[PDB]
Length: 33
Length: 33
Length: 33
Length: 33
Ligand SMILES: [Zn+2]
Ligand SMILES: [Zn+2]
Image 1: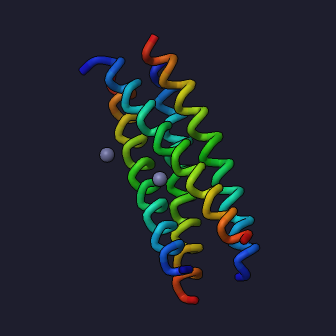
Image 2: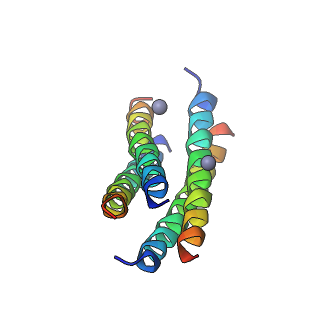
C-alpha cells in the first residue's frame, strides 16, 4: 500500500486509541472516588 | 491492595494510549509528507 | 459496580489487542519496502 | 527512513499488546474484588 493509505489507517487507529484513553480515564476517576 | 492503586494503574494505561495516539498522528503526518 | 467495570475493561482490552494486530500488519508491510 | 517508522509501529503494537493484557489482568482483579 501507498504511504497515503498507510497514513489513513494510522489516523483511524490514533483516534480509536484516543477514544479508549478517555474511556479508561473516566473509569479511573470513578474508581479513585 | 487498595482500589486507588487499581485506578492509578488505569490512569497509567490511559496515559500510554494518549501518548500512542499522539505518536500515530505524528507518524501519519510524516507519511502524508 | 465492579462487575460492570470489569466488563468494560475487557471490552477495551479486546479492542487494544485488535489494534495491536492491525499495527503489526501495517508494520510488516512498511518494513518490506 | 521507512525502516525507522516500521520499527516504531512495531513498538506501538507492543505497547498495545501489553496494555491489552494489563487490562485483562485488572478486569480479573476487579471481578474477584
Ligand atoms: Zn513517544
Ligand atoms: Zn505491565
